[PDB]
Length: 89
Image 1: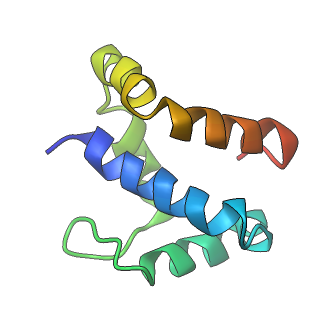
Image 2: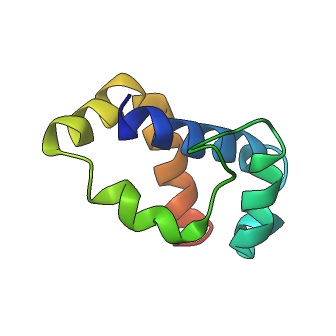
């Protein structure tokens, strides 16, 4: 029911498709989105729009921040390593 739920699905499915596979699409991040939606990644009745990042981050709490990291620290470090090394969104 959370934004954590929402977001971890974004990040993890993204991560899997970038990590040992296809980085060139995270480059031009619209290409990324539509290969990630392809999977069966669903949101609010609809496919993902990049505009809704406002609806992502604002609605998370500190509680949730900690959590996101704490539960899937493997995935946090995973993308954090990608972030500094490849390219900053």
